Length: 38
Image (cartoon, helix red, strand yellow):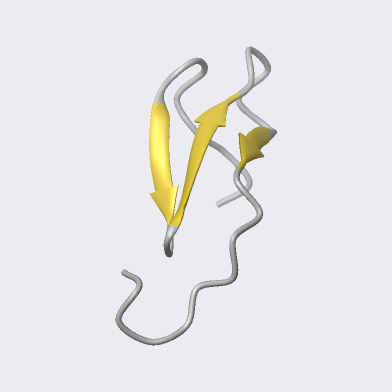
């Protein structure tokens, strides 16, 4: 599960990610995700 759809958004807990063109990396926000944030 070291993969995503290249160029697509996903949510990781409270943080929103965009999959890299290689689909083996994501640029994500770095917010802490305390209970009820997601």
